[PDB]
Image (cartoon, rainbow, N blue to C red; front, side):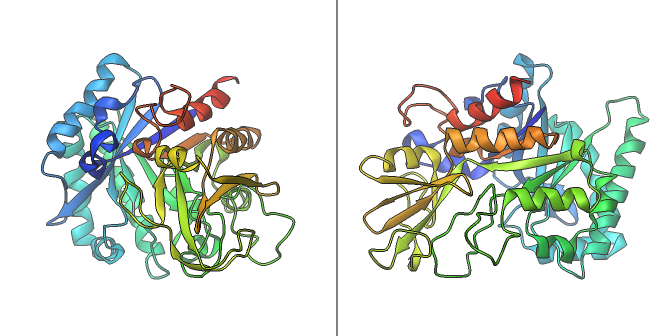
Length: 361
């Protein structure tokens, strides 16, 4: 079973214990660690943070302790305009130039592959995304002729039905990618004012519209569209989403006035690291949707939808019963990497939980 774990560059700038460097990653925890977000300049892959070259090296040395550990660099991200991606992929001239610049880069810095995080291709993009994957993979195969292990190629894909139908030719790209990560944790819609969970596992036998907004449906669909189970990786969140209640109503459907207040170390409205959530739980009321099998907590006018050890193990068993390739954990830097916030002195509580399920068979 694969365990793809993402590490984000900007997590180094968090204050105090919030600060996280590759240094803090247990080399034996995941099977693959993806460095989050390389960039593109003059149609060529390129760094983003001033010291990425140093962190790259720091991350790739973990391989010294664990020979089997594989690493990848991800291109794109949210702070990366989708238009920018779209523009590079539409013109075969800029596309080939981008493709050609990748192998030398990865090879220089010690990565074993590239991860595409084109965050949401549009209806006019489907054709070009296919071209990108097809030609990139071809370049990788060609480069291996030089007698070196072929570079891996994966992609982070949306889990919303509409999003999928609009910009992805799944049957096509599935056959060229080494693995596909399902962003199965952006199900609640940032668009409207209502309390709701972003990573439901199941549909929930209690609300008709938007049955397409849960992990189970997303997986079943990808499988229907032609993606082999042995290439699908289900995404599991290590963070939680916060909202500021607009009323004393805490139950499902409760009105929302906006995002929850920022966290002491995360400093971003609507988001909270799992270690921040561990501190938040103190004096909070904990609830759990039985149908979706995910929890939430409330304290004051703050409503938080998150994932704990049990919801995470739950998702992991699901993943196994459907025989997928494995799990993908978004942000190791959002988990309790120090292991000093969430009671139990365990390091990487959430990611470990997933690993435990995947390893007992």
